Amino acid sequence: EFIIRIPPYHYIHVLDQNSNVSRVEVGPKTYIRQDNERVLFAPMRM
Amino acid sequence: EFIIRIPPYHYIHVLDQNSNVSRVEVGPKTYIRQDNERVLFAPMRMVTVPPRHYCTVANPVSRDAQGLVLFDVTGQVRLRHADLEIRLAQDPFPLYPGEVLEKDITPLQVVLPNTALHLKALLDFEDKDGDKVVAGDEWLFEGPG
Amino acid sequence: EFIIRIPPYHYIHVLDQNSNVSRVEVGPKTYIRQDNERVLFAPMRMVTVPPRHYCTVANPVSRDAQGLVLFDVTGQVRLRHADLEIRLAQDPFPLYPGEVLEKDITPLQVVLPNTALHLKALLDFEDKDGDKVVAGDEWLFEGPG
Amino acid sequence: AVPWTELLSLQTEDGFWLILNLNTNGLHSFLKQKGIQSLGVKGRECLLDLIATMLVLQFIRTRLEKEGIMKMDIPWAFEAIKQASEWVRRTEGQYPSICPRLELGNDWDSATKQLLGLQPISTVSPLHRVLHYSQG
Amino acid sequence: AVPWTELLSLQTEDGFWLILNLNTNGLHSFLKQKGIQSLGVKGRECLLDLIATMLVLQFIRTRLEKEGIMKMDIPWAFEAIKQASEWVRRTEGQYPSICPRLELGNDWDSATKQLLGLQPISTVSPLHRVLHYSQG
Amino acid sequence: AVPWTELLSLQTEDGFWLILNLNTNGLHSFLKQKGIQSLGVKGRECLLDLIATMLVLQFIRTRLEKEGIMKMDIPWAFEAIKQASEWVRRTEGQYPSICPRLELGNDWDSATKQLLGLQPISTVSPLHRVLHYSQG
């Protein structure tokens, strides 16, 4: 669950549950979330 | 689970799972943790020590010239490893994480008149008289005190 | 498996399978490995040594004039093979890979008064007095120290 | 109805002293912890003989007070009580205040009666591991 | 009810000393590890005889204190106790402080009572492999 | 309960020394490997008789210490022990430090007790093929 691999030209939304604030991460990057954070859905294409 | 009510003169330890760093919260306060954080145990009393008594705590707090608790760059507390510090009568201090209460509240011993104590120096130190007390030395502490 | 949480004053060893090279990570930090990498074992405590105590570790760390850990060109740590180094009271150092903790935390021995130690030189060395102590020599270490 | 002739069998050849019903090994451990080795081996044995003699005297005096009756001096043991009093009133003067400094009591009445186990002892005193260690 | 006549059989021809119930081989290993060969063979045997004699004296004194009763000097063994005291009070002066330097105790009471096994020993002392090695 | 009269049968005609329970052939191989032929045949036999006599003395002394009791000088063997002590205290002076140089121990206590097999020997010493070669 914790490991998030964003393919090139894809994005996700992850929820900061200490702030109730969501945000996007883009790019051909790998992502690691926190305990508080929660990725909303699977990596969809930009 | 999320609601934490610290009674007056009590403390807990809570673990920052984004840093693997634990910390104390004291006082008559109410506490709310995060999703990442996890309180380790139920609120236990800040240990108090009466007059004519003492205790020793393993791994004491590293402090400055004024007695402020020194911290790490990573939010951790600064200890002195495998040492023991003897604490006299004072306010109900808390126990910072990574510390064990080895000696309990034990009384200061009274030496009766016409009776003395045989004391050995375990480690080389300097006494308040002014002599470099080498380890292995022997002492004669007598008196009614 | 991928998430690695190193507690404060703990370490692990992880294997770079693209280089067959292992390495230590210390500190109160969190760790994420790669696909190639593999953590060897669960996070164990950096071994601490109190005062009036010592330990010996097989295959010690090769160091520079300042005590920095020397490394190999291939990312490996520089050892000194089949040697033993005796470490006195210090901070909780880690054990770099390829090292065995042979002697545990054992106390510095005290010599009672009117009693001495019979010491043999196993290997030719030079003592702090200034004599070339050839192997096979015998010693008389007496004292209350 | 304690064995009395067996008490007459345990009279020593100089005049001092399981029938006594007391934890002797815990008492030796207590007196060793209080530091009785700083008197010599002769002084240690001379003090243990005094403590044992006064303990037997307090036991017999509690027995006689339950019947109703340095002043101990029945026809069957008048000689042993007499030589015990003549021993004690000579050997006590070498050790003044040895009952507080070994932490047994104020005087010999307090010390031997609190070690005899017929009176309760307060909680602030360290005399708890001599009467309750034998109850295991 | 220890065998007493068999204790009278083990009186030596000079006046010193399985019935004692003590690990003797582990005790020899402990005293060898503490370095008793640096006294000569004569000095080693003279010290072992002193340690064994004082161990038997502490055993008999614990037996007599459980009954209630350098000052050891019953009619059936007064001569053996007398010659043992006359031996010990002469041979102890050659070895002052031999109980701390061999790491058995402060004085002979502490050393012989902690080797006798009737009192518990603290954990920082190396006296654990003499009373617990025989429990296998 | 070792055979004692059979030990009295093995007293030699000058006063020196399977009942001993020791690997004798492996001991001869060990002492030959340590180079005992460089002393003459007379010196070799004089050293083997000393080693065997001290081994029997350490065996009997371990037997007497388990019962509790150059100073060895029971009525049934006082003459043999006396002449053995008078032999040993004369013949030991010819061979100083023969126990380290043959690699058996520091002194005669260490050497005869580690060869007797009642104490464990450290692993860095070459004394392993004398107590474990007989266990096959």
Image (cartoon, coloured by chain):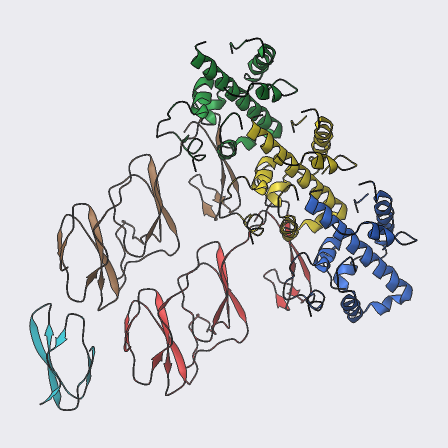
Chain colours: A cyan, B brown, C red, D green, E yellow, F blue
Displayed quadrant of residue D50: top right
Residue located at (42% from left, 40% from top): B128
Query: What percent of the width, then of the height, locates residue D49?
Result: 57, 24
The answer to which image quadrant residue C44 occupies is: bottom left
Is residue D123 in view from this perspective?
yes
- Residue F95 or F77: which is nearer the viewer? F77
Residue found at x 43% / y 27%: B144
Q: Is residue C110 left or right of residue F74?
A: left
Q: Position of residue C52 (x, y in %)?
A: 48, 54
Residue at (77% x, 66% y) in the render: F27
Q: Nearer the viewer, residue C26 or D78?
A: D78
Q: Position of residue E125 (x, y in %)?
A: 52, 47
- Above or below, D52 against C9 in this view is above
> In this rendering, does residue C75 appear at all?
no
Residue at 48% over, 74% down: C62
Residue F16 location, quadrant: bottom right
The residue lying toward the viewer, choosing from D59 and B3, is D59
Q: Quadrant of the C terminus of chain F?
A: bottom right
Q: Is residue F78 above or below residue C91?
A: above
Q: Nearer the viewer, residue E36 or B96?
A: E36
Looking at the image, the residue that sits furthest to the front is: D1
Q: Is residue F39 above or below residue C98?
A: above
Horizontal arrangement in the rendering, residue B95 relative to residue D30 (left or right): left
Q: Position of residue B60 (x, y in %)?
A: 34, 52
